[PDB]
Amino acid sequence: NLKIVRMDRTAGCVTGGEEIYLLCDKVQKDDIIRFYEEEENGGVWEGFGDFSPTDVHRQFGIVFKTPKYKDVNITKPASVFVQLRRKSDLETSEPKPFLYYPE
Amino acid sequence: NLKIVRMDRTAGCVTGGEEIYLLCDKVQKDDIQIRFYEEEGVWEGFGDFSPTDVHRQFGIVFKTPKYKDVNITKPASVFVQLRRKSDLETSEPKPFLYYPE
Image 1 (cartoon, chains in turn cyan, orange):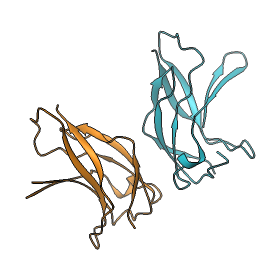
Image 2 (spheres, rainbow over the protein chains, first blue to last red; image 1 turned 90 degrees about the horizontal axis):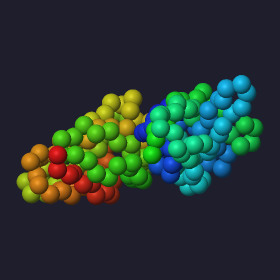
Image 3 (spheres, chains in turn purple, orange; image 1 turned 90 degrees about the vertical axis):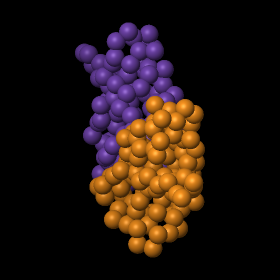
Image 4 (cartoon, rainbow over the protein chains, first blue to last red; image 1 turned 135 degrees about the vertical axis):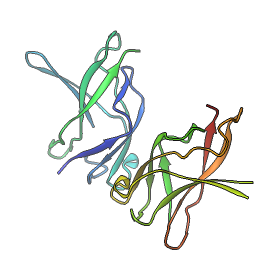
């Protein structure tokens, strides 16, 4: 169902606000980007891509800005995951890798 | 009919070979081209991509062509248009900046 096909960037500054173009299989502009890192003995950090319905290009693309990472003071890169997700039923795509690098 | 809606980069090195994501209205993967051009005589360069880089008829991921002169000292502004191979129809242009190496 949900699939990320490709992204123009797979790395970003921990400060977020960087624009990325994502090409996906069919989505609905008002019912659709979850950055997440599975944390060590249970928890899960998440941040969401920033964009509006008009940024969803013809159901097959999304232009958005990255969320800020959980810790903007890291000195070494942090490898996290990115996935599509639907608001209506919280179903998701298989995750893609994303690399947060220090400021 | 043809329309460039947006591109993730509107500038690049004269050397070419830089990847760009272009979002467009409906195209046919086997009947589409991306033409960079400059009136002089007319210089043209074509986005480098395969039919499989045309994403669901609504986007094209490609690599920029090398500009005509790699030794420019100041940026050269050109146009980019989508163009159908069959009937040569084109979109409205967008500006694109080639900067010095």
